[PDB]
Image 1 (spheres, helix red, strand yellow):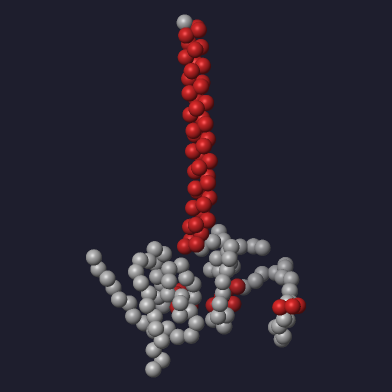
Image 2 (spheres, rainbow over the protein chains, first blue to last red):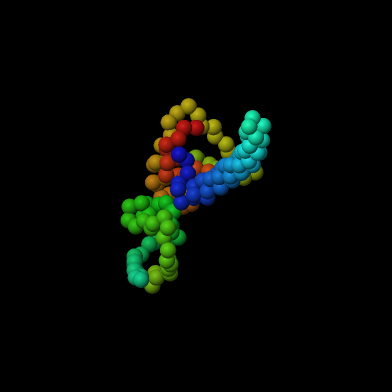
Length: 49
Length: 48
Length: 49
């Protein structure tokens, strides 16, 4: 609302870079946690079986 | 692929306002450059 | 202003509780240099302060 595009690009680019980096970190940690949950679920299935 | 020469004359202030993302009376009413302009801008005094 | 204060005692004037027309001053080419940081001068009239 308060920045002309041809200079607001750098600000919004910093914001998008940071937010996307945060999203990548969240997704990566979720992937690792889901791998752990997969191992636990396979163990649970083997135990039930 | 193609090159275009645009020619005009400016006096007083705003002599350097012929640039992408600039503001001014001439930039708003007479001639505006695009946001992602590629090219060159040339200016020189010609009072004589 | 009738007289401008020197930088040693630069004059400060509070502005509040009104509506301000930056359009006239922006269009007026009397100001040789008009450099705005953090806000775009074109839509400076849009916001509230």
